[PDB]
Amino acid sequence: AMRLPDGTLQVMVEARARAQVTDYIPGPYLRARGEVFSEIFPIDEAVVRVLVEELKEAFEKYVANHKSLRLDRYQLEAVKGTSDPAMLADTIAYHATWTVAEKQEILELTDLEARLKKVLGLLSRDLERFELDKRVAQRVKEQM
Amino acid sequence: AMRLPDGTLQVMVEARARAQVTDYIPGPYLRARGEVFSEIFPIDEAVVRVLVEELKEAFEKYVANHKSLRLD
């Protein structure tokens, strides 16, 4: 909780669980109503943990190749000691930079297991994007 | 079978054996005559228990492959 009364208040929040937005209250400033924490999730958590291990593998492949995103290696140092698959899945989903729409659709889906598949798909998409970025780099050099 | 003071009849059932059906009785409500309760006993259980083990292994593999379903 940083107190900066100069036009920018920096509040760092650790989210607990998603909830359904009931309605909206016109502002400014705006309000919204929500339900209790989303404590219902699918099971077969063992395969979810296996997919968490594979997600750590994929994110290690990601950040090591994605050094042009200026993302520090410290973000690869926090996936150790993971006591819950959901926190690691969300951390990897936010720590990889792409369009805000995909990051938000990661939140909107209440399915625990489909979120990991979405994260893996988007990580592979950014991987192939980096691959063709390199490809067109040498291609444009050859064009010169 | 216990009463719930809310508007729902709460009764636990458990099937024991299947019975053949001969004819129906007009309703409401419906009745049925029970002729026999046919259910074969396990005879020469070696093959039966081998298939039981295989069936349980197959069901375990069925449970271990959920990605959009929920089974406890």
Image (tube, coloured by chain):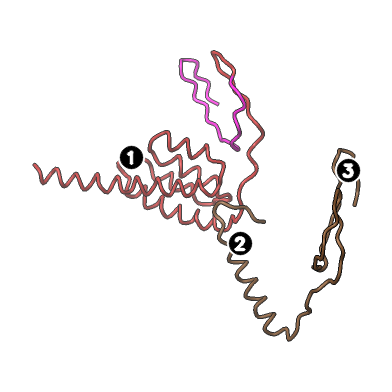
Labels 3 and 2 share a subunit: yes
Of labels 1 and 3, the one closer to you: 3
Residue at the disc numbered 3:
B4
Q: In which quarter of the image is the N terminus of chain A?
A: top right
* Chain of residue at mark 2: B
Residue A10 in the image, given as x and y percentages of width and height? 49, 25
Magenta region, residue range = A1-24
Which label sits in the foreground, 2 or 1? 2
Q: Quadrant of residue A22?
A: top right
The local secondary structure at tag 1 comes to: loop
For image coordinates 39% across by 47% down, the residue present is A123
Instruction: Answer with left or right where residue A144 lies relative to residue A64.
Output: left
Side of A141 where B72 appears, left or right: right
Q: Does the magenta stretch include residue A16?
A: yes
| Mark seen at residue A69 | 1
Kind of residue at disc 2:
Val
- Which badge, 3 or 2, is on the more N-terminal residue? 3
Local SS, label 3: strand
Residue that mark 2 sits on: B63
Viewer-side residue, B62 vs A117: B62
Chain letter, brown: B
Judged left or right of residue A15, residue B34 is right
Q: x%, y% of residue A9?
A: 49, 21
Asked if residue B49 lies left or right of residue B36, the reply is left
Q: Which amino acid does label 1 sit on?
A: Leu
